[PDB]
Image (cartoon, coloured by chain):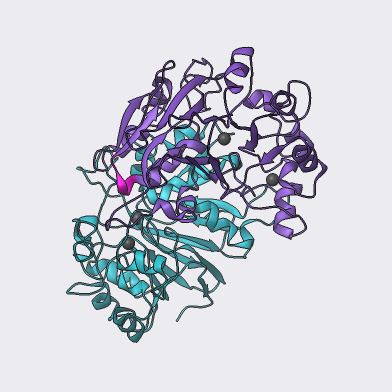
Chain colours: A purple, B cyan
Amino acid sequence: MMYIQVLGSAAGGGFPQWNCNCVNCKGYRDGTLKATARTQSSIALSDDGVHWILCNASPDIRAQLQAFAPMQPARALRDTGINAIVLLDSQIDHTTGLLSLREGCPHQVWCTDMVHQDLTTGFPLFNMLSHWNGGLQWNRIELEGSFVIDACPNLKFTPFPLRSAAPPYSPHRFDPHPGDNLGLMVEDTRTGGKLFYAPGLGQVDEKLLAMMHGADCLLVDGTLWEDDEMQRRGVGTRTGREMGHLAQNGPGGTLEVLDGFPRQRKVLIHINNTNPILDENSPERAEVLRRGVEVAFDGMSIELLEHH
Amino acid sequence: MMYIQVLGSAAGGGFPQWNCNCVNCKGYRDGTLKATARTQSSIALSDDGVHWILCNASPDIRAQLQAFAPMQPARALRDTGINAIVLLDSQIDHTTGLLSLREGCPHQVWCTDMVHQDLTTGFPLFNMLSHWNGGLQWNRIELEGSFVIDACPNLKFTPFPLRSAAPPYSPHRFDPHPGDNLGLMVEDTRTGGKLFYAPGLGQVDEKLLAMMHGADCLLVDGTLWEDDEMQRRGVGTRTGREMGHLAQNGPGGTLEVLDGFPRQRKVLIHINNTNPILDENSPERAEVLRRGVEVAFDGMSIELLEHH
Ligand SMILES: [Mg+2]
Ligand SMILES: [Mg+2]
Ligand SMILES: [Zn+2]
Ligand SMILES: [Zn+2]
């Protein structure tokens, strides 16, 4: 059994975003919209339900850990359910949470060379936190092969490079390298059950589709409904293809991609505050439900029993 | 009228702390303790109730802004009540929140030379955030004289250096300079009402006591009840005098200091998760109340009408 816990399901900024008064964020505050608040994307994995692996550490991490009981087993005066942390990129929304975990250092952190470089230069988390009882102990994620964290020995992670979208602070935002962004394939080596996790998805080729058909659950990018969604809300100028996000609707959309996977469980995660799928009375939400696609939410439990 | 809003009232780690199972943190989780959860220290100031000045930006800033309506006036699709931010030090618990405000850059940030140096080197917030539409616009806080932020033109800030307790990540944690830590004197130039804000207080001399008697409200360090509180809870080895905190109880304690101020309003803020004053049925809470001292809490409103 693989326990998957959605701690956060919103894109950077959360929902509602602190400075946004779009139809969703204002509709939530005014109470004229059936929607649920969401923290920034983060999931937790376990093979036993006691030892947990954190995938990305959001700025909302303190609230995310409180809301989930197994994170505090109370086995000692100082304790936590987090046994390791895996980083998919060096983005602010996925790494800032590490600052809030300074009291429980050291931590085993799994990231790539490129992420480790960003987190030792532009955003030197590894250098800052080292002053807290050991800090972050880096475990390299090589772009090939697989890795197993000793706390969840039945979990097999097989990373794959996705199209690079390096953070703005990054020394090489203008010079993208493989290793800037990862999608994860987690396998329960007891059952063969596979999870395809890719909150940041901006390009999908035929070799990516190949391994997706070997998965049982697809947990992927759901940031935007339209590529120009930020303009249609009048809160931004950036498009999904600029930010490296494949929108649900349109040609080469996620809904077009996911349509070739009728046998897999399909969940949209990392959802921006402007996305109408957050509105449960929205026709967009209807089309998503109609296609057998779920909209992740804070507190969602995904249990992986077996392979099909 | 000076509007003072306590966004956060806990010391670093908040209450309860994510990894702590002391008598307070566990007593809260078990429901066997009458106490209220608290976010990390942060207050907001205003002279009109519309334009707000943020004093320190905690990691819990997203929740702190949500809980307080005037932070989102909804005057445009993109808006906020924060017009300026003042930093008292370069500590993680007071600066990390700036990362969560990246969507609404630029911001006018008020800090000292030494804080600006820490926030451009060890924790380069000013360098990172500049990639977000201008980033942080530094306004120097000189260690003498006063300053007025144009958004609250009736508020007069007069900073004073306190005993230096530079952060662990800081290049000069071993080489303390004046300007590492500030206490603030805010004056309503319409009424003469003065606020003495000093969440980090580890030493008090006769010249500090002098200006305290010119204040109407004392908003000061309430981190520990005893200097060896971390040892008595069995969760730490550090003492208050090591961390630069004057404990309430004992010789040279805050309660001993505050005893010479029977005419001022007295509020304890920046309170650690191990402090028994968080327990409302505690004899420590009783002694604090008996002396006319209040225990700050998240959501507390302090209104300064006049001078006495
Ligand atoms: Mg993001
Ligand atoms: Mg602190
Ligand atoms: Zn919005
Ligand atoms: Zn505690």
Residue B58 visible, this angle: no
Ligand 1 is found in the corner quadrant, namely top right
Nearer-the-camera pick, A292 or B226: A292
Horizontal side, residue A166 vs residue B117: left or right: right
Nearer-the-camera pick, B302 or B284: B284
- Where residue A229 sits: x, y (%)? 75, 34
- Where residue B276 sits: x, y (%)? 31, 72
In terms of image quadrants, where is residue A303? top right
Residue A96 visible, this angle: yes
On screen, B146 above or below B208? above
Circle count: 0
On screen, A200 above or below B196? above
In terms of image quadrants, where is residue B102? top right
The residue positioned farthest toward the top in the image shown: A206
Helix, strand or loop: magenta stretch: helix
Q: Residue at x 76, y 39 (%)?
A: A234
Q: Residue at x 73, y 29 (%)?
A: A255
- Where residue B208 sits: x, y (%)? 28, 67
- Where residue B137 sits: x, y (%)? 51, 40
- The quadrant of the picture occupied by the C terminus of chain A is top right
Residues in magenta, as a range = A102-106
Is residue A269 covered in magenta? no
Q: Residue at x 66, y 34 (%)?
A: A222
The residue positioned farthest toward the bottom in the image shown: B290
On screen, A239 above or below B126? above
